[PDB]
Image (cartoon, rainbow, N blue to C red; front, side, top):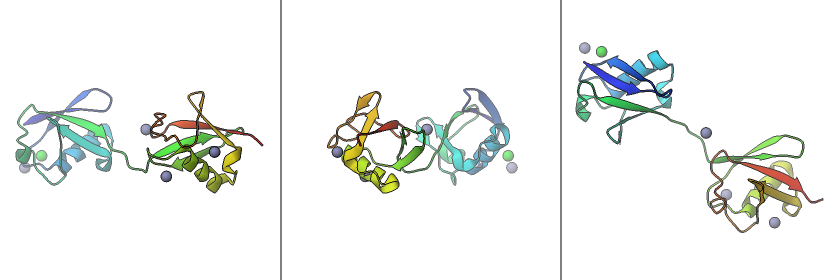
Length: 149
Ligand SMILES: [Cl-]
Ligand SMILES: [Zn+2]
Ligand SMILES: [Zn+2]
Ligand SMILES: [Zn+2]
Ligand SMILES: [Zn+2]
């Protein structure tokens, strides 16, 4: 019995499996071939994220089925703030946070009063009271901090 895995490079690997092989077992096989650890794997079949403890047969995964591998990451929503002198601050934020909130977080880390902070995103200077969501600031976006002293 063989199934196919569409890997993270774009390629497709073949795995020799058995109907009762768990998803956990499949993740091990992938880690052997692609060298990515099971904790990092999310396996998608026919629109369904697959569960570690269940078997191929529980999911009716038949010969020649194609599993899609997706990278799995873990961490609170973060953004970066670059300084005049190239230090990068990492911040834990939420989509609803206002720029006011973000300035309070900068004061927390670096001790700069909010009223001395100017924050820029995609060349655009941000206004407090508007949220990160309004500006389309996503996880791992980068803000630039400028100071009115
Ligand atoms: Cl086997
Ligand atoms: Zn066996
Ligand atoms: Zn917040
Ligand atoms: Zn302000
Ligand atoms: Zn990322």
